[PDB]
Length: 605
Image (cartoon, rainbow, N blue to C red; front, side, top):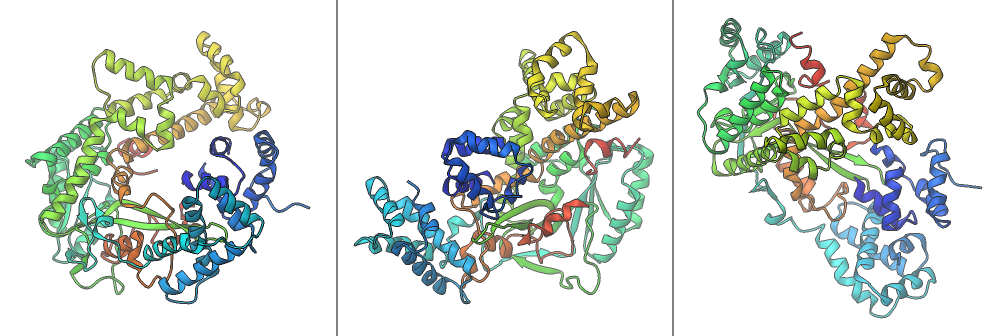
């Protein structure tokens, strides 16, 4: 996300590295609407000419940005500004020629701009020193193209074009240690499935409406297996017997994973999942979705025949529009759920942001390659649990980066080392929960600085410290409520209770912001996504090209066609977008997961 923003600010916003970075700290990653058009960057470039303070100040007084419309050695920025430069039109010439080779139809205007800026930036990356400055002045002064510049540009042209024409080789298709094959040799079932449910309520093994969903899945799936993994240690004896009979009467294959005998990685995952479930039962920060996230990848849980993992409540495309054949094929042994979102980027092609999820995972039958990919995932998740503080420290997650700066977090680490205890994930989750149970521990945990900036009063951080010190809680209350109900006048219209419940809701929201990554980043899909990233080019953004003659030149098209569950199952998920979904259609997010704090404080009480 951030990489591109900074590129824009340095190419079109008149910023340098340093002040472009300062700009993003002074700028939610909802900034990104400002870049689908030039308007913000054009005006910010005008203010940039008069110093960084000029731009900074314009931003704080501007009512709200995205409301910006026109008024009344940067080779790349010069190539896109100066449209009549004999060099810039030899770039556009080459851009259009490359496209008629690599494309299927008559190039779009966005499609030439895409290749054009590719050429321009590579030319900026091939020139350096005085020969960079000379051609920058040549761009601005519309001097004719230098001799032998068309030979500097020929190897560039042939690479952008061959990058968009050749099939990616096997070294760029290595996904979880297994090559993504284009002939789809791996076979899958559309009928076998398993799901997982570790109840936090010993007297109710599984909610009734999820039981109904599984009764439907077992019936639709015919003779295929509908497997349900659970933990006997989480139920009462009476409830377990009821559960076992319910599964028997509805064609559901129960697997009590407590009885599994595991070795190697399997046993490492089994031990960690049992630890989570034990810490859940004891009210010590354990989470049943974290346990499910791990048990997902145990070989004895998955089994030997092709089978899909699905979330227990995952619906199905039952009927005349479903897949009738029991067997399908794909190019990888482990198919994760994938989609992508298109980010508008002005006159260029839209950026394509791929999404990964573990809510559906299609496994092929037992084989060496499936074992390679599974172990690659398992080692990752096990590695996250053995190095909790090291992962938080390196995390790219914003909420986890903030966690590393909180004094309560530093204090927690010191206690653990003073008492020679390694910080466990449940320990951290437990600690955060307790900390968010009152305003005072909360402010103490996060620090007054952080508190002050959150409630709009950075200058009062010393004041909050003293009130904290001497125990004057009403100022923390009122400072927080005043930021919530927009003004100190409004807080006075409220009694004890309505102000006390606005603080509980707010504290709960802040806890969820940290709780959610404390599952997803270690055992969940974000941890799985971190293991997959290495496959993606990291050097230019991925753009959606609609009609490549060879679509298998782009990694996202290889993933979409050969390494994901799309078109390979009857299960229907709305947790991530479908492939190439417009950023607007990802408004779907507008209208608490079963495993977060709230809902888990419900599913028994």
